[PDB]
Amino acid sequence: RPVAPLAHAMSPSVLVPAGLAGIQDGRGRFREIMTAIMADHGAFLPGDRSSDGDGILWRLAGEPGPTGRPVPLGVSTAGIRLVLVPGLLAECVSESSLLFDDARPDVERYGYATTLVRTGGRWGSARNAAIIHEVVAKLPENDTIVFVTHSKGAVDVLEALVSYPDLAARTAAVVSVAGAIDGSPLAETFSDGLLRFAESMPLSSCPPGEGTEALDSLKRAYRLRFLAEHRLPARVRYYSLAAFASREETSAILRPFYDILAKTDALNDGLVIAADAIIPGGTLLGYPNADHLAVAMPFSKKPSLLTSVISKNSYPRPALLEAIARYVEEDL
């Protein structure tokens, strides 16, 4: 695309150390919690692996040490409900994959209720925000609501919190997992024609979108403008995990997109750059060593061409989701 229209749409933005955008560094305590969880009951959890070194969570510079304070490893009685919100195209592959599906037995064992929200896989954030608003309105009043979101789901939820003060007042926390907070430059990379055809083609698992509504929601200019123009509700707590893996531990299907992003930032999960995946003013929990899909969306149906090309899908999602729940309960 010629640069003039992109320039006109872009709001001034700056890449800064996390501290300068009001981010609390919770990387040390989160590593501590997740590591203890896996030492305590990781052995039969799907995706179990060594927690040593960068195995589960990358060690970026400046990481705080462990606090030494005991990690809760029993059943929660806090009445917390994790409201799971998926991202782009998730609805379309629902037969093969549901968000954190293999992690929900483990967190429910330990006292955390879970609800999965079905969003439009090909719909814009405003339309999905209304869906989320209606779902949460029907959840039990005494539950403590903690969103756990993936990809576009994160900004579906942020737009909802900004649009519906009653949802904001109802919500204790939002956790972003590889959330597309600043969108992705890939949303602009491909032709409108291609995006329009993808939006409108008949699929038996997800309804079509209008125009390019879903991708419009993921454009960097749009997403940066949202954050420039709307304060996130202050009474809600925000937390972010930003995934990336090495090229060889990145799924085949994601590698061509990884390769585009890696031209300027190797710390990307295939679809989202890590610096674009952190909610400003929130808490940074860390960097799962996993590509965009492995960190949150299990694919296991065999055989499947789809499952086969998502070739690096193994990650300890149950331990990750349990660590998220325990960190937020502790932080709250």
Image: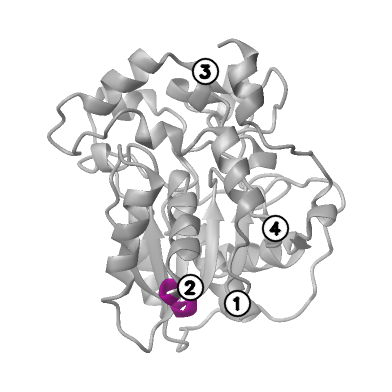
What stretch of residues is rendered in magenta? 166-171
Considering depth in this image, is 113 or 215 the residue closer to the camera? 215
Tell me the amino acid under the disc marked 4. Answer: Leu
User: Label 3: how many residues lie within 10 Å, few (<14), some (14-19) or many (20+)?
Assistant: few
Tell me the amino acid under the disc marked 3. Answer: Thr
The residue beneath circle 1 is: 235
Note whether 181 is above or below 26 in the view shown: above
Q: Quadrant of residue 247?
A: top right
Return the disc, 2 or 4, that comes first in the chain's sequence: 2
Looking at the rendered structure, the secondary structure element under dot 1 is loop
Q: Residue furthest top?
A: 2
The residue beneath circle 2 is: 168
Residue at 31 percent across and 41 percent down: it is 123
CA gap between label 1 and label 3 equals 36 Å
Q: Quadrant of residue 182?
A: top right
Tell me the amino acid under the disc marked 2. Answer: Ala
Q: Tell whether label 3 touches label 4 (CB within 8 Å).
A: no
User: Label 4: how many residues lie within 10 Å, few (<14), some (14-19) or many (20+)?
Assistant: many
The residue beneath circle 3 is: 189
Q: Label the magenta part by its dominant secondary structure.
A: helix
Return the disc, 2 or 1, that comes first in the chain's sequence: 2
Note whether 132 is above or below 90 in the view shown: below
User: Label 1: how many residues lie within 10 Å, few (<14), some (14-19) or many (20+)?
Assistant: few
Considering depth in this image, is 22 or 100 the residue closer to the camera? 22
CA gap between label 4 and label 3 equals 28 Å
The residue beneath circle 4 is: 284
Q: Tell whether label 1 touches label 2 (CB within 8 Å).
A: yes
Q: Quadrant of residue 235?
A: bottom right
CA gap between label 3 and label 2 equals 34 Å
